[PDB]
Image (cartoon, rainbow, N blue to C red):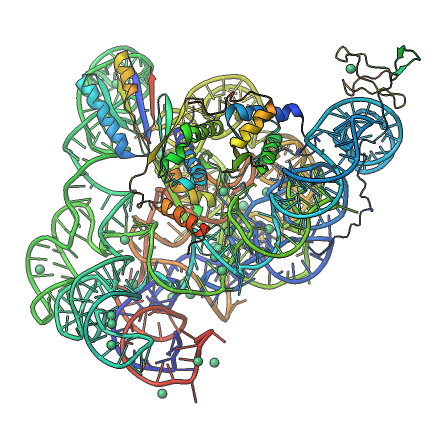
Amino acid sequence: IKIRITLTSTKVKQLENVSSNIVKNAEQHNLVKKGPVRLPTKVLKISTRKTPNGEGSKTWETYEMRIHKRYIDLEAPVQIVKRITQITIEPGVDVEVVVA
Amino acid sequence: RKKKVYTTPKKIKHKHKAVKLAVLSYYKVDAEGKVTKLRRECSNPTCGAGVFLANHKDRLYCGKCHSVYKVNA
Amino acid sequence: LISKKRKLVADGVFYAELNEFFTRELAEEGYSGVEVRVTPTKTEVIIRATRTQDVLGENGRRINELTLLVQKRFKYAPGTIVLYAERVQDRGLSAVAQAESMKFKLLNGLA
Amino acid sequence: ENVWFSHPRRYGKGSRQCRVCSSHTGLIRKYGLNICRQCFREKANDIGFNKFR
Amino acid sequence: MLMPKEDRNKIHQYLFQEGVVVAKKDFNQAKHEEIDTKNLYVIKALQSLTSKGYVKTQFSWQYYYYTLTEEGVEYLREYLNLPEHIVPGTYI
RNA sequence: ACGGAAGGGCACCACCAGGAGUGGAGCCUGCGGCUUAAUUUGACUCAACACGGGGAAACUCACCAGGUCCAGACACAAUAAGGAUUGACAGAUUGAGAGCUCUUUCUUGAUUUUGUGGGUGGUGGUGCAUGGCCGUUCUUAGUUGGUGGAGUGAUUUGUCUGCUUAAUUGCGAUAACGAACGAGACCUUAACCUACUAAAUAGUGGUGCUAGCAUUUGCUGGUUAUCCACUUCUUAGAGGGACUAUCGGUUUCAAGCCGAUGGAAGUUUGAGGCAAUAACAGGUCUGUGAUGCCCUUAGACGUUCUGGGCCGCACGCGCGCUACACUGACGGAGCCAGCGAGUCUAACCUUGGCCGAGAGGUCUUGGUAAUCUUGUGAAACUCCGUCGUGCUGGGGAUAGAGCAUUGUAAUUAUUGCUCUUCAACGAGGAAUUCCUAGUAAGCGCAAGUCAUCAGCUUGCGUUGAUUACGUCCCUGCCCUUUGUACACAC
Ligand SMILES: [Mg+2]
Ligand SMILES: [Mg+2]
Ligand SMILES: [Mg+2]
Ligand SMILES: [Mg+2]
Ligand SMILES: [Mg+2]
Ligand SMILES: [Mg+2]
Ligand SMILES: [Mg+2]
Ligand SMILES: [Mg+2]
Ligand SMILES: [Mg+2]
Ligand SMILES: [Mg+2]
Ligand SMILES: [Mg+2]
Ligand SMILES: [Mg+2]
Ligand SMILES: [Mg+2]
Ligand SMILES: [Mg+2]
Ligand SMILES: [Mg+2]
Ligand SMILES: [Mg+2]
Ligand SMILES: [Mg+2]
Ligand SMILES: [Mg+2]
Ligand SMILES: [Mg+2]
Ligand SMILES: [Mg+2]
Ligand SMILES: [Mg+2]
Ligand SMILES: [Mg+2]
Ligand SMILES: [Mg+2]
Ligand SMILES: [Mg+2]
Ligand SMILES: [Mg+2]
Ligand SMILES: [Mg+2]
Ligand SMILES: [Mg+2]
Ligand SMILES: [Mg+2]
Ligand SMILES: [Zn+2]
Ligand SMILES: [Zn+2]
């Protein structure tokens, strides 16, 4: 029934908690799956002069945002599908469910 | 800021205030009592025969189709 | 239909604009931060304050005002945005709150 | 009139400004956040940007 | 500032119906969202309203959040010719 | 605090031993002065001068010559529906289909206009009136209470003679005891895991289909719905691992130091982030709808339109890019990375096909991205040849002409391309900068600014040396003792 669930968070602990509860749910329902594939955590860099004005030693500041992306592939009926989208929500964690 | 010269002409020249001419809305009326019409009106179906064209000279200027009607008697 | 990078920086800018709006509006009510939990069926916004009674107002009037402002500003649909208020734990362990208290005291004229 | 705001503002430093300070100089246009560098340094920990190295 | 009565009452009836209004601080926009009137007219009408105690403002990143008071809702009732207790933005 | 006083200990923003250099030429860029209608302005030792993320056509923009608008809220008074006021075709006028203003009349109808007060705005002044941020003193190891003790007191001890350490880090000694901050611990990153979890958005092997050469099994390849199996390489998540381990020397024989072995890793493993007290009358009101005061506030210093300028050049400095050639230029072949960015109510990164010498144009395609651009087939590099010590095929400014692209607009060339012109420069004087290993240096690539414009910056990787592993001689820092007629403190 070919569903992909992608999770695109910044918080590794919340993301892994979500992944763990999803996979153990699918395992106690005994659903075939491709395990949680962890894509490269992508770093968003922004380099800025530390100062508002221009004088001083040219001190630079690199701010980073680490985006962690996981995906899981499930074979599942419509009931388990609708309840899985009902649940597996935590703050700061964004989900995308797509069929086919 | 040193000073302002205003080498421009002495030209504080702001325009009219929609010059306060006297009472208006003259079509005009006969003695007891038939009415006539000054200020020949427009040719548009949107004009409900209540808007006066102007007549400056060699041109009649509208008020409803506020500018576009121009063939002069 | 937006990339995840820009999606997340938009989430961050949304949180920041909300924080600034609330720390300008509800300063007299002990605004000690906000949380934003998006979800299927809605996004909920949990304000953490002290004077929750004054944040609510009568009949949730001010909460309705703020929900409408947020919706109109951020182009949400009516019903897709919800606001909750919560009495913050450990009022003394919140720097913004004590700073606002200092501000109001120094403005009222205390030393 | 029709000359009050005539000049196009489709590109250049006049087509953009900080969504906070309404300033044209020093824009961070990366990732579509459009914030001056100063206000970015102010609001980074709120936006989710942090220093690690 | 001078503006047409239909536009002023558009602003006022939208404000009475909703309870609030948000206006980007972008003059020369010529089209407010959710109102067919100029954003300049919106902003300055509600500014005139602010100065006489009826409505209140918060700028917050160039957006002019406006919300009305009891004086404002009573004034707008008297102005829009509506009955006593018709509807504010105060329904539970 | 200072000392051309002593003692001890440190630093390639100091030196030694050297490397690459800059200063010398051309050009780019910033600063000054000069010029100018304006050539906006801030910043002047380190701690100003490729800095204001400042690569300015317009905007940006603050400056100059001019022209509009009002966004002057609100209150009061006046005028005033026998009309407050608004707008307007055409012509004159104006750079200008700005009624801006005037001619002429039309249009609108209480929102306004005039005045008074009072506000609003200001890249206007004050950074010596402030906030916040940053930089620096200061990348060193220093700072502080409580209670006791010394002193009339300011103050001191604690916070130390020695040894040690990168380190007031420790051993310890001891009128001090017990604490705190900083340092360290911490966090991130780079290096190890053939051990865990797995994964057509990363791979590998085999088996099907298939191309070629050999044919005797084999070798090289392709192949999305051929599946099967796996996770060494790749990705991460949880964990392990190094703690100077073991051994030998050296030290009151303590802290610790040196050498060797093992190990992926033994300079606090490497590089960073965070980073104390006290201060500068450092910078910044030109980041802020952060701001007091002053000024201005409708022929406004508000705002906006047009056009110029910020590039203007007899000169002087700073950061840099090109080079002065054979360890080389050119032409062909060979041919290898990594950090990253990318389209929504839009038009981004663009493969492939065709056209064009070229730039580039066009028809399509994929990608909201570990999947597509992109193995980013980068450059230096290597191999074959041409040249031959000749300001030469080194070098490529300065100029002429043309073809394209970006953009409303390129004229004081935006940039790209083609041909031609082919200047200085023959290794750089007094001086002076950076640097101790995957570092210097060479080499290019991505991103930032960005419609276009890199010679700049932030990072990435590719090739990869010499020379110390020490000292306090110069320039400075730290602690102690000492002298001082210094205290804005040599
Ligand atoms: Mg030397
Ligand atoms: Mg050189
Ligand atoms: Mg220094
Ligand atoms: Mg300009
Ligand atoms: Mg201009
Ligand atoms: Mg101005
Ligand atoms: Mg100062
Ligand atoms: Mg200051
Ligand atoms: Mg005492
Ligand atoms: Mg005593
Ligand atoms: Mg004491
Ligand atoms: Mg095969
Ligand atoms: Mg031993
Ligand atoms: Mg370290
Ligand atoms: Mg400031
Ligand atoms: Mg300049
Ligand atoms: Mg510099
Ligand atoms: Mg040549
Ligand atoms: Mg070659
Ligand atoms: Mg690669
Ligand atoms: Mg030196
Ligand atoms: Mg670029
Ligand atoms: Mg330019
Ligand atoms: Mg620059
Ligand atoms: Mg050394
Ligand atoms: Mg003496
Ligand atoms: Mg004295
Ligand atoms: Mg002297
Ligand atoms: Zn008509
Ligand atoms: Zn800003």
| Whole-percent x, y for residue F316 in the image | 60, 64
Using the rendered view, name the quadrant where residue E24 is placed. top right
Query: Vertical placement of F257 versus A40: above or below?
Result: below
Q: Nearer the viewer, residue E8 or F402?
A: E8
**Residue B73 shows up from this direction:** no
Q: Residue at x 36, y 35 (%)?
A: C52
Describe residue E52's horizontal placement relative to residue B71 as left or right. Answer: left
Q: Residue furthest right?
A: B31
Which residue occupies 35% across, 46% down?
A: C95
Query: Between C48 and F138, which is closer to the camera in this rendering?
Result: C48
Query: Is the C terminus of chain A in the top left, top right, bottom left or bottom right quadrant?
Result: top left
* Residue situated in front as seen by the camera: E20 or D11: E20
Query: Which quadrant would residue C48 be assigned to in this image?
Result: top left
Q: Quadrant of residue F218?
A: top left
Give C34 or C4, whichever is nearer the viewer: C34
The answer, for residue D51, to whether it is visible in the render is: yes
Residue B55 position, x and y percent, is 87, 21
Numbered label tally: 0
- Seen in the picture, residue D38 relative to E9 is either above or below; the reply is below
Question: Which residue shows up at 33% across the image and 20% down it?
Answer: A97
Percent of width and height locating residue E35: 57, 24
Question: Which quarter of the image is occupied by the N terminus of chain A?
Answer: top left
In the drawing, does residue C97 fall left or right of residue E75? left
Q: Is residue C63 left or right of residue F192?
A: right
Residue F450 location in percent, x, y? 54, 37
